[PDB]
Image (cartoon, rainbow, N blue to C red; front, side):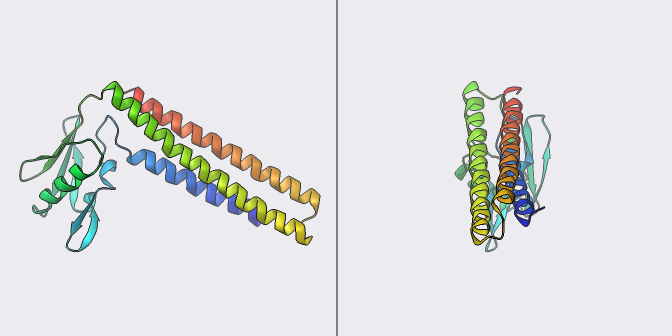
Length: 184
């Protein structure tokens, strides 16, 4: 528990959680209310995520029903969705907004898998950045003489081990997502 190692675990864990989050909100073949968490609508002066203005549920195994209590929000949700890159078409019946998820095309799966991979690559990059920043902080301490050479090397090795275990975890969450997308 060098404050450095503790620090690396904290930041790397946070990075990994953000990635799992992004992968979780990603539009995929099956309906998931999670994809609307990033769709904001300007409601009474405030950019508002859709799920905060409506109950969201799954009816037809392939449908997302978005029911807003303020019926004037329907128009806004539709506008916002068409403007996003979800690749979904709102079905406004004046009461609720339906989002159907047709069987995905092999070109869509390939697109989504590519999108998951890039989300994860960015995470990896963040991981390696954390490693670099800490490593130099350790080097600094080693230069002032606070951390003798030997103690500095094992500290770096620990950081290197953490980096590898997190890069691995990233590769894993990517595989898990890739499977979810392909195993339809």
